[PDB]
Amino acid sequence: MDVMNRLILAMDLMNRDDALRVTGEVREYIDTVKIGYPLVLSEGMDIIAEFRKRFGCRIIADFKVADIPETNEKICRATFKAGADAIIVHGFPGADSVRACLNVAEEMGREVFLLTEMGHPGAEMFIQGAADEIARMGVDLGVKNYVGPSTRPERLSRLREIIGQDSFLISPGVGAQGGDPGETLRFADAIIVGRSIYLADNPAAAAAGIIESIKDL
Amino acid sequence: VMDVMNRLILAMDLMNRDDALRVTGEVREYIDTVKIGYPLVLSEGMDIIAEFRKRFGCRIIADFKVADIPETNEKICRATFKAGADAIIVHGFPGADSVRACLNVAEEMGREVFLLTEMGHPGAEMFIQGAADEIARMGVDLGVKNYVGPSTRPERLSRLREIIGQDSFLISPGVGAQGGDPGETLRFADAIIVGRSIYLADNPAAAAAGIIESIKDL
Ligand SMILES: O=c1cnn([C@@H]2O[C@H](COP(=O)(O)O)[C@@H](O)[C@H]2O)c(=O)[nH]1
Ligand SMILES: O=c1cnn([C@@H]2O[C@H](COP(=O)(O)O)[C@@H](O)[C@H]2O)c(=O)[nH]1
């Protein structure tokens, strides 16, 4: 996957007008947008097609898929039907639940991104201790796309070690949550940035600044 | 705790508005509580909740298995309650702060959180099962009063009931298609969740009636 400027916009605004306007302001800096439930549940799944029509950008649905296999397949089908190019799935629920997603992605020409470890404080309670095993499960299942935490560069580095240099890795937690753009890119192929951009007084300048700090990479 | 008619909750996972509405209407005389998940919501929009409320006199539980960071969890809960959902199901594996974020929104918006402590599919054995008891204990500590546990694992469901106490409310999916027995599950759960066994039946009403007939004494 070729992500422009190695920067993925996490568009979590919950108003269609603001979401479209802000994304439009930073469109020259990106070509990949991560859309999640905050926006989809507020404005509908048709918003995905609207983004493709207005920006011709890649769409990653950050839906943290975490249900039983049967339901996961239905969720992936509905998501890809709406035009998403990829979907983010939790690994904690087990291999069968991940496989269900991989099946639908293969049938509709999309990609599955396996979320192995999250970066918020609570992730240390249960997720962190299972993260390495979840990553190995991904490798065993043939997963090639992963999501790891910018807030814990040592954990992100370990994830990269497990999956190898060939796998694709994206990482949220940059900016608002404290992650550093440059350091995160030492291990991840692309960084995900939300609030530091869409809540900034001037989103375009915010995006430009981040890219400027990593222009060397 | 919510008074679930016949201790039976319909898992409406059909992905077509016409079929979802028709089947729910066919069993309305037996159920006043419907669980709506992403299969239907992502196919027809959150306004589907409005349609169900308008057409039927049923409570709505949004099975969204919320599993994001605290900030995103808050946004998801706000959007879900804004649409009319009475309650939302949240995953506990992401930790205490992520669950607390949901409880805070539920409290401010006057709605409820159901904590999913353990799942019943085969894959649940890998990581979820070993963390379930602690996730349940965490829920009790956080003040959670509503829980979701697996009908497919009677031993696990029984332990969950012990951990949360008799006052807590517990609902359980996995009955029917996944092999769980209605009566056996109700020994521990306040209500059972049933999807395919009802919505894929030639006559959903007859299927619902049959299940209720098997637990009449309960
Ligand atoms: O471990 C994870 C997984 N996902 N996200 C998601 O990535 C984005 C981060 O946005 P932010 O830059 O505004 O913090 C949000 O959409 C959030 O749900 C995280 O923050 N951390
Ligand atoms: O541990 C869990 C948690 N949730 N569900 C959900 O409960 C319903 C079960 O439906 P079924 O009767 O068709 O199996 C579906 O909506 C499914 O996502 C399970 O099956 N198991």
Image: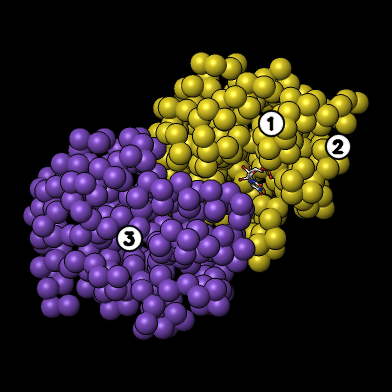
Chain colours: A purple, B yellow
Picture coordinates of residue A38, whole percent (x, y): 36, 42
Amino acid at dot 3: Gly
Residue annotated with mark 2: B183
Amino acid at dot 1: Ile
Which residue corresponds to the image point at 51% horizontal and 34% vertical from the top-left?
B16
Most extreme residue toward the front is B202
Q: Nearer the viewer, residue A89 or A176?
A: A89
Q: Are marks 1 and 2 on the same chain?
A: yes
Picture coordinates of residue A131, whole percent (x, y): 52, 70
Residue annotated with mark 3: A173
**How far is mark 1 from mark 2, CA to CA?**
14 Å
Q: Quadrant of ligand 2?
A: top right
Please give the chain letter of the residue carrying mark 2.
B
Residue annotated with mark 1: B9
**How far is mark 3 from mark 2, CA to CA?**
46 Å
Marks 1 and 3 close (CB-CB < 8 Å): no
Asked which secondary structure carries label 3, the reply is: loop
Which residue corresponds to the image point at 73% horizontal and 21% vertical from the top-left?
B30
Badge 3 residue CB within 8 Å of ligand 1: yes
Please give the chain letter of the residue carrying mark 1.
B
